[PDB]
Picture 1 (cartoon, rainbow over the protein chains, first blue to last red):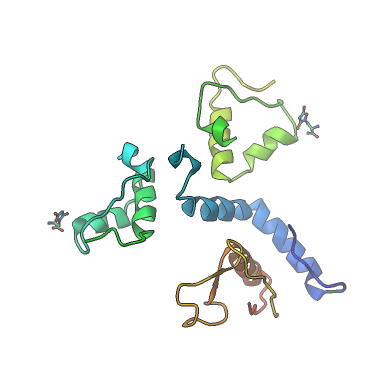
Picture 2: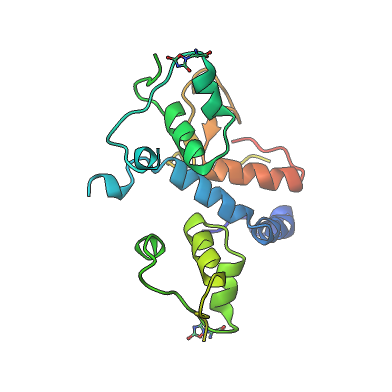
Length: 48
Length: 48
Length: 48
Length: 48
Ligand SMILES: N[C@@H](Cn1oc(=O)[nH]c1=O)C(=O)O
Ligand SMILES: N[C@@H](Cn1oc(=O)[nH]c1=O)C(=O)O
């Protein structure tokens, strides 16, 4: 999964640097663990 | 409450306005946090 | 890994220096975080 | 900067009062919040 930039976009370099800065802070990961798991209310444990 | 928060078979409601509901709002214990994410996520409303 | 991280019967080790150990160091997924808190808490050392 | 996003949970979701809120306030989700952390740093106005 990647950010789609048009061929010759001015936002080809700053978006790619924004990709790195969110990753270096783990902010990509701290969004993923938050949104999937506060919504995970039917955790598979409950039917088991 | 650890046996409460780990099973979603049972619903958890408190009063519409009181010292109990506000206690779980400003709480930051992980067990107490996970309950308040459930108390807000009420379909239908758990509160009375 | 969810069935890994929820049971401490099994031990989890990786290489002493490589891309796998460092992947769980800078990770911030909650399942991946809880493993790295266990990987550091190794008596004896899980790593090889 | 016109941001095209497709309508699919959990990446782009509809707010509860989606007829009431418009534009950026209408849309919630993961790619929405991903757009906000990028456009904060890369300084561009984003329209969803
Ligand atoms: N009296 C309490 C309210 N309350 O009523 C209950 O039945 N539980 C409870 O916390 C307060 O001062 O807010
Ligand atoms: N080749 C890997 C190291 N590695 O060896 C394994 O057996 N697993 C593993 O991640 C690297 O480039 O760090």
